[PDB]
Amino acid sequence: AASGSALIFDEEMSRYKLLWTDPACEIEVPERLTVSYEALRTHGLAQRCKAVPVRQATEQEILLAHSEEYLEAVKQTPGMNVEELMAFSKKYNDVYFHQNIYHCAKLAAGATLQLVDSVMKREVRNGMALVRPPGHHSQRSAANGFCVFNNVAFAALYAKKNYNLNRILIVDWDVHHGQGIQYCFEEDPSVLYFSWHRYEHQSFWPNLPESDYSSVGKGKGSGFNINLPWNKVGMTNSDYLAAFFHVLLPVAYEFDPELVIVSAGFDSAIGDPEGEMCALPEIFAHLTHLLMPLAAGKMCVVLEGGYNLTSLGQSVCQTVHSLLGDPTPRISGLGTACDSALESIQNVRNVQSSYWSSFKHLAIVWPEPLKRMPASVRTVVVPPPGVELTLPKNCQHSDISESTAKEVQRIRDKHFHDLTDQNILRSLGNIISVLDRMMRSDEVCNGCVVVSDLSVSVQCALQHALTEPAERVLVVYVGDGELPVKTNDGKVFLVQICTKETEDKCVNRLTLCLREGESLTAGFMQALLGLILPVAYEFNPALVLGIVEETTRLMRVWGHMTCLIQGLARGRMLTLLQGYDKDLLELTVSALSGASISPLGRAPKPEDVEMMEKQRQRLQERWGLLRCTVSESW
Ligand SMILES: [N][C][C][C][N][C][C][C][C][C][B+]([O])([O])[O]
Ligand SMILES: [K+]
Ligand SMILES: [K+]
Ligand SMILES: [Zn+2]
């Protein structure tokens, strides 16, 4: 029922700045705020987001994560001259104070709480706050690393108290370690904290042993703190997505959070002087997109770092774009993570194996991003004739025109001479016309068509896709038969989920024979996050073809599959379901349209996880993004 996204911002938070020479804080400028908000307005994104006003965080809220002694000291900074602010700032590590910074710090915190209440009251689906100062270095009795009050720490504690939540996920993709957040929830198993960060074997600020992968949390909350230390600069999109597919997402989906909060620092993006990483601004479109199936989309993005003003504006727009549900950009050039990334991926999964099921079995210029825009109508639905269905506001039906109708006639005489059934012939007329509207017309994004004959339906859908043209087509098929899909020219990759064990010799095919049982859904999510998504992302298809046979435990997982796989091919996925299932049809259309996805809530069987790692053994040499260990030098 929730809909819309909140952009919380105020130009007042850009009215404090550094007043003395200090190279350790020159980069933290108020223009960070003004540049990103105007980039949002230039690209029409701010106008599409509900503008919730900012608040001052009350004293009682500040005390949720900070001591009275520290709050009292900061409260005295508006009365200091610059000499007294200099002396106050040198008592902390890499942070300056301003006559207005206490004022803005309360606003940055209140803005985060305004976002939390807007999302938890269902007044919006999600949102982002553009705050300054940052927060994730702030500690209970200390300002640290440009941070005065831990904004993200407030949101989790605030959401814990006023909405009695049991599970909150904090994802810190800033290039720095959010040690303030880790310290505050170290023993809290209700707030699962994840942060990747430039570590460089503890030689990069803040130079803490606790920033390493060793720190899994303390006491009752052990295994609820996950650090992924980057030990080399120049991390790429492949490293960031390997981090998601093989660490964060497996843990995040077993945790099943009731709310997601993102410490969104964009100093991890290309060209940032502080992070010195190499991920493109488009990567945050996918980091955002891959998280939105969690907690029914309840996601609050809070700004932290990001200092290259061009790199910063581009990354902000890519995040709000995916927040609004716009199609994701195709990511080209994906491959294996570097050896150093694979080394830290390896170590985190090993130490976390005591706590998380998906691991237990182990025991400077760049191009400007292409324009992103929602389709005129996102999803087109073709139910059987005479079946009227209630459809969301961005979903239509079908009206085959003369030229499309002649194409099915040409196809019939060539490959289907005996095909006389006029019901199949209408399905092929729709398949072509919606594919025509998805690929070339750009007015439609995706679509879903109910079919009668599976064999004929797949050929026309796939063959008409390749000549339109579609450089690559990923085919995801839930069924047991064989399909008219040739997988040798490197143009097609086939994912098959079946009930019969089968051997695969082609390295462009991935068959998963998952054991039938209660285990089915937990094992499917592991193969989705750890095998299907990494391969599909490296493949970079131009189109996704979903096929479901009539012979039903797909209901639980098919929604997240449809939502997550829409990160590929700019979200242009056409689904063919054999036979009419009102619930199944309404589920895919709901997921294809960009609606909220209902959550899941065990652990899989070793018979299945072994089948999956053998698939990984068989394919990771070709598809390096599958790798979760360092390759062995011969
Ligand atoms: N170029 C010199 C900066 C060095 N001082 C530490 C940076 C703290 C980072 C804060 B944040 O990016 O997490 O917001
Ligand atoms: K981080
Ligand atoms: K924790
Ligand atoms: Zn940072």
Image (tube, helix red, strand yellow):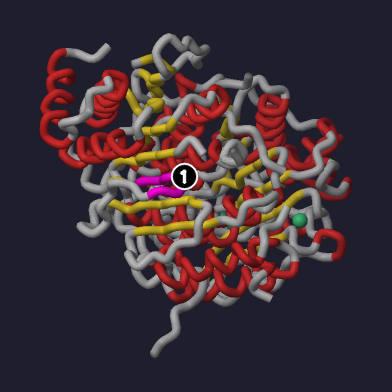
What's the amino acid at mark 1?
Val
- The reply, left or right, for residue 467 in relation to residue 542 is left
Above or below residue 45? Residue 62 is below
Above or below residue 619? Residue 382 is above
Image quarter in which the N terminus is found: top right
Q: Could you say whether the residue bearing mark 1 is in a helix, strand or loop?
A: strand
Looking at the rendering, the quadrant in which ligand 3 lies is bottom right
Q: State whether residue 302 appears in this view.
A: no
Residue identified by numbered label 1 = 478
- In x, y percent, where is residue 439? 25, 31
Q: Nearer the viewer, residue 289 or 112?
A: 289
Above or below residue 586? Residue 356 is below
Q: Which residues are magenta?
A: 474-481
Image quarter in which the C terminus is found: bottom left
Q: Residue at x 48, y 35 (%)?
A: 550
Q: Residue at x 32, y 50 (%)?
A: 540
Q: Residue at x 27, y 29 (%)?
A: 435
Determine if the magenta segment contains residue 479.
yes
Q: Nearer the viewer, residue 415 or 152?
A: 415
Q: Residue furthest bottom?
A: 634
- The reply, left or right, for residue 290 in relation to residue 519 is left
Above or below residue 54? Residue 363 is below
Quadrant position of residue 582: top right
Determine if the magenta segment contains residue 541.
no
- In x, y percent, where is residue 445? 35, 28
- In x, y percent, where is residue 35? 43, 36
Q: Residue furthest front?
A: 418
